[PDB]
Each structure stands twice: as structure tokens, then as C-alpha cells.
Length: 154
Image 1 (cartoon, rainbow, N blue to C red):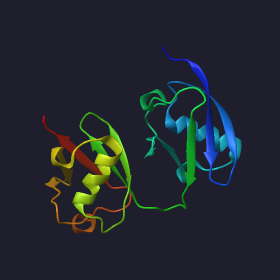
Image 2 (cartoon, rainbow, N blue to C red):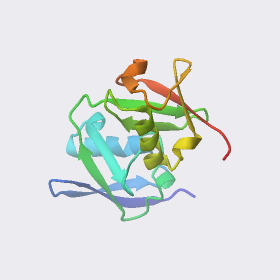
Image 3 (cartoon, rainbow, N blue to C red):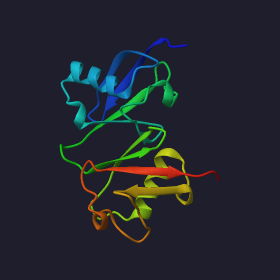
């Protein structure tokens, strides 16, 4: 069952703030609360917990975040290249990438974030399977491009 709790958000410059949240609040909503309190635009915010960046559309409970847990808040300048990898289940995996990142590095980033072995991943963009040894730019994948991730049983 959903419940109320307090969490902490800490920036690198030393401040810990307390937020009143519900266990099923989304990360997007937490970023909105941080904007309301500190004035920081959500698109500049990256929230980190268990060493992973937290996905806007998932909830605190999805990440096992409990009362008096702390989230790191790291801030980016506007315009860092992100891409969105979406499974056919609707899951979204937002990756900070560079324009010449190799496909196998993208799969390695997906493994770091989601635990999915690279050999189980099939990435698709514009109807083409993305091949190891090629780069994002080889497929004209650029900022805010959306890729599909297809998975088979191990």
C-alpha cells in the first residue's frame, strides 16, 4: 500500500533538503517539488540512487526508496545529448550519450542501468537493427531520438 514518507535530496554544494512525498510519487513529481523549493528547472535535474539515474515516469517505490533515504541531485547544463530507449512493454530508459557512441557501448549503458545483458538486447531505430561496431551517428540518431529495445527469453 502507498504511504507517506520524508526523503532527503542532497546537492553537491552541501545542502540537504527534506521533501514530503508519497511512496508512489513519480520521479517527475519529485523534480517538480525540487523546482518549487529550490527553483531548479526539472530538465536540468538528474536524481541518482543506488548509483543509477532515476527515470522520470517511474515511482519512488519502483526504486525501493524508503523513509529518510537520500537522493543525490546532480545538475546538468541544458542540452546534453540524451536518447530514449523504449521497450515494447512501455518501459523508458533514458541514456546520456555522445553522438559517436558505439552501439555496444549503448547496450553496456543499458546493462548498467537496467541489468539486461547486452547479448539479450536488440536495438531498433527507423526499422533497422543497430549493429555492434557502428555508432549512433551512423544511424542519424541524435538528441532526443527514441529507439526500440526488443528482448527474447534467455
